[PDB]
Amino acid sequence: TGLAEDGAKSVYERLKNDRAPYETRAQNCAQYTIPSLFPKDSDNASTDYQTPWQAVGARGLNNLASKLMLALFPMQTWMRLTISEYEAKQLLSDPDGLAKVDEGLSMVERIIMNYIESNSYRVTLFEALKQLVVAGNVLLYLPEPEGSNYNPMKLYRLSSYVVQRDAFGNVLQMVTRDQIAFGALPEDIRKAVEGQGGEKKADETIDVYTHIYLDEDSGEYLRYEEVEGMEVQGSDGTYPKEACPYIPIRMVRLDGESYGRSYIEEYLGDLRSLENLQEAIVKMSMISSKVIGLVNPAGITQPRRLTKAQTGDFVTGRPEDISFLQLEKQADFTVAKAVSDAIEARLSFAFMLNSAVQRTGERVTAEEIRYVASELEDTLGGVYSILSQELQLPLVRVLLKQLQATQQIPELPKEAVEPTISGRGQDLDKLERCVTAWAALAPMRDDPDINLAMIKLRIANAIGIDTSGILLTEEQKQQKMAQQSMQMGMDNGAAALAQGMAAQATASPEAMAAAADSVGLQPGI
Amino acid sequence: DKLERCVTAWAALAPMRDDPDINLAMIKLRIANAIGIDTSGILLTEEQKQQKMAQQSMQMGMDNGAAALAQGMAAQATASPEAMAAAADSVGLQPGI
Amino acid sequence: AVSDAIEARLSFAFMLNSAVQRTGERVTAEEIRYVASELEDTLGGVYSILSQELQLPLVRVLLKQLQATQQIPELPKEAVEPTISGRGQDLDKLERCVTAWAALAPMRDDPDINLAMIKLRIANAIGIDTSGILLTEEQK
Amino acid sequence: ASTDYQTPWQAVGARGLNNLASKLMLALFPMQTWMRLTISEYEAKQLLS
Amino acid sequence: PEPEGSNYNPMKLYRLSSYVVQRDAFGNVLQMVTRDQIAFGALPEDIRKAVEGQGGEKKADETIDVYTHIYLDEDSGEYLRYEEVEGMEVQGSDGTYPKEACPYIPIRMVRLDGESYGRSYIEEYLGDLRSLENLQEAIVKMSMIS
Amino acid sequence: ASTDYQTPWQAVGARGLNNLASKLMLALFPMQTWMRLTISEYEAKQLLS
Amino acid sequence: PKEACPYIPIRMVRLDGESYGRSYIEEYLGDLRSLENLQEAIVKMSMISSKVIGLVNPAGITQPRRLTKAQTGDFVTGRPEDISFLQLEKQADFTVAK
């Protein structure tokens, strides 16, 4: 069918002329930090990536992709499922069923963390976060789960995908190119390539274009994926607007333009300037490294004699003839060093690295100033905020739909949504502060006038806990009272007849022989 | 915070709780007025005080009562060998042990 | 001074605390030993891929090969493995919540607080599985 | 067998490799267990009492 | 190596001078080859029947190099491994390794798309070391004129 | 898409903005509840036992 | 209604009456703009510094022709006081602008 589009190859080729602004930024932007991270398309096995003269960009990227990772994808749970609490009160008999629902929400949030960690999503997100700093865009495809086998996700680094979005935030169409070799192509595709005609080599590389365009009708995406000239049979799929396995991440997203400029090309000009200093300081040390012996030619010493002498020889000559050429950029080496130590100082706050110990003399201070290192957290925070909506949430949503279809998760009843909280958190700390307040009420527990039944409610209201099942109701208090009595009833009762029976059983010698026969024992002891 | 500051003031009144002359029923109101808490349900009222007195007794009534007949029944149930066989049949158990 | 500056910016690239041959005095406290602690992030970036590449394959191969030689029980087709850096999460989440229960020891005898419910909520919050955690009616 | 490997004039690469292959080893292959087997918990609830 | 009994069974490493793999621009591996040159005496039994089966006597210490080939079968995406001595394959070499569980796994660090092997970690900073050496070569040589 | 944004020669404005948009955020939209609903207390006493 | 509309304009440093409100960081905008003109000059003073020009005294003996084919340790003709290097002299001036 026509499908209301030209063809995925073409869509990829018309809009490949829109990556070329961002792509030639990232090729420049990875050149200064770490050249192995965003290779130019021409680059191949042969290309050697010369290290930059400065090593702050290589430092301040791993020290920022890692901090971002810890913050965004903490090992400790980083999504939780909030049920809408008032609509949970209506559809349910309070209060035991409410936390029973939140156990099912604590059920799911552990299974996803057991799904993310057991499919190496921590790996390909850290490869994503390194692309999000240098390049600024990555597409992460969450392959449909097929069985409980190993199923890793895939990242396309803005050299293998194309998206097109609006001035408005929503995505219109996506294209990705992967070039899977003939042997490795999935079955249904091999029937289409052979169905096109002509034999192929086992290692010949076939490139498959998907096309994830927004259907005009229904705002549900359509995805058809295409090999060589035309579409594979069975490629057609429809992804709803809120749950599609292809989600493009962009950092520093700017209106409206389709991809988002990288984080480390914010300070790219400044790095580029740091490099031109650190290129010159090293080259000043190389003129220094050469050892030239300037012989004064109006003198007596002849190097001919100086160069066949042994360890201790007496040689003719004056010492003031032999001088050595030395570099004189001294009051100049300190100019270019103190600026390079000032540019590294103002990039080490821009990146989340505490600044290099090579610094001003002494001057190290206390925890107070380690609190300035603590203040580096705000700087960490601004960059990860967008990342959450862009990456954190989509991944969670896609996972939740995909686990319903493979029945690895219970079908949660259409009303639970998720905040990627940095993780309760608020449910733990608000229990605890209030629980200490109740001990503050331990001395007054026996007090005649203070309404301890009310103060425990007020402190709760104030911390903000839900109350509801927190206070024993009257029925429950009555039950508690009987249970202390039924304990002492069972305790004194079982101690009564056991003293009661065994006193009058063993009483009298014969009755004693009759009592042992009821168990099964003999008369003699 | 206004709950808490005042709640510490009440512990400052723990040593004097048994004092004969200090109106501890009034000092707990004044500290409250001063912190600025709403009072109102803070102080047990007459009905509540009576109920609390009663509950300590109904606790000791249920506690000593349930310990009485359980010592009361089981002493005279297991008293005598035959009455003992009759008592085990009411639960459902056999005569031999 | 250039060779002491190039060794300084390779000693952070490698996971070695930089050579003591350095600027005079200037040694500081645990706070700055926390910068040595921050060397862990740099350690982390390089080992992440290594995990998928080496850690997991070795474990998978070992698991199949131990089934064929009967040195392992045939695990029933549904268990998968995360190379966690090791529980870990099963130990620490037990423990934090277990301290919270002692925080509830003074109030154990309190007439109004539903201690049967607070022990459930703290559990829900730490994130432990509950399920067998609370004695049921029969067990009580 | 004959080749003699001349030591480099700098000894940071010889330092910063053993000090990085060892740290990587401790981190990746800790003596303490470094794999654990997660059973799928919801499918474990279904097939079991 | 496949466990054979509860005896001692160490694994083996081939350091990019003894193996060859070929993978796609996509992440998956197509074919692997390794060369080990086990001497005649040490060659495992079934291989000695193939080398003698080729013909001609061998010295006890003459070194024979055995190529394995771990190519991805076009059919079924299950690997096939046949290993070969001199000109042709040993009897019994054939084995089939599923895609997710094969005893030959190539590790690569700093894996880069798509190219088959991955550039080393310490050649990230290789330029910088190489520059450190040219200083430390000069400081030592200045102490020798001294 | 083409425009390249040259970094300013100083990096205090880039520093002092993220360090001020973040502090403002923590202060204004704290994770801990930052609105509460006051009922008019005297009119709540009248309409209620 | 007047009190509940989904479009609410936020303005910071709201000034009477004018419709939008001047930004916070253009309070100190003049001052930043002045900081930039210093930090542009300090960096450009380090770039003249970065260039390494070998000023040979042309009334001397040393000839750079010999100095530039010498190996690591060669004995070469000449006086050391002929070869000097041009260096930037804004020193008591780099500390004013810093």
Image (cartoon, coloured by chain):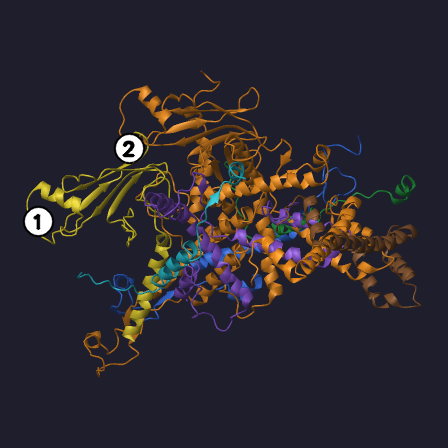
Chain colours: A orange, B brown, C purple, D cyan, E yellow, F green, G blue
Looking at the image, how many numbered discs can be counted on the residues? 2
Q: Position of residue B12 (x, y in %)?
A: 82, 66
Q: Pointer 2: what residue? A: E73
Q: Mark 1 belongs to which amino acid?
A: Lys
Q: Position of residue C88 (x, y in %)?
A: 51, 53
Hey, which residue is sitting farthest left in the picture? Answer: E56
Q: Residue at x 62, y 31 (%)?
A: A413
Q: Which residue is nearer to you in this view: A462 or A32? A: A462
Q: Mark 2 belongs to which amino acid?
A: Asp
Q: Secondary structure at mark 2?
A: loop
Q: Pointer 1: what residue? A: E58
Q: Which disc, if any, is residue A296?
A: none
Q: Quadrant of the N terminus of chain A?
A: top left
Q: Residue at x 47, y 35 (%)?
A: A142
- Check contact, mark 1 vs mark 2: CB within 8 A: no
Q: Secondary structure at mark 1?
A: loop
Chain to which the residue tagged by mark 2 belongs: E
Direction from residue A126 to residue A495 in the image, left or right: right
Direction from residue A525 to residue A34 in the image, left or right: left
Hey, which residue is sitting farthest top in the picture? Answer: A1
